[PDB]
Each structure stands twice: as structure tokens, then as C-alpha cells.
Length: 21
Length: 30
Picture (cartoon, rainbow over the protein chains, first blue to last red):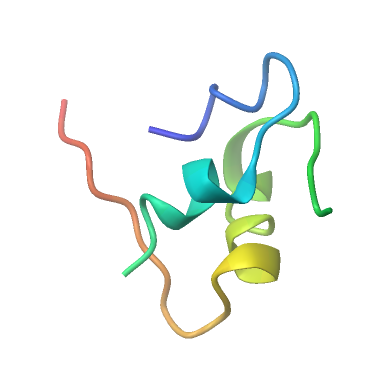
């Protein structure tokens, strides 16, 4: 889950979409 | 694009910038 995934290096929108309803 | 660096419930605010507003979720379990 995308708490930490971005908290490292830089992250895309498809990462962010994943979780979304 | 929108892409960032931060942690936590800022990837909610990134989710809000990506997907949109209206109630938006989280799906893993621990």
C-alpha cells in the first residue's frame, strides 16, 4: 500500500490509481 | 505530471490529484 512506496523515491499515477475505489 | 516524494496521507492528496475526490480508498489488510 502507497504509504511508503512514494515516501522513498518518486512515484507514478498508476501506483496511486491502484488503491482508489 | 503530478509525481512526488512525500509520505502518508499525502498520497491521499496525490490520489485526489490523480483519480479524484469522492471518498477515495485503500485496499490492503495487516
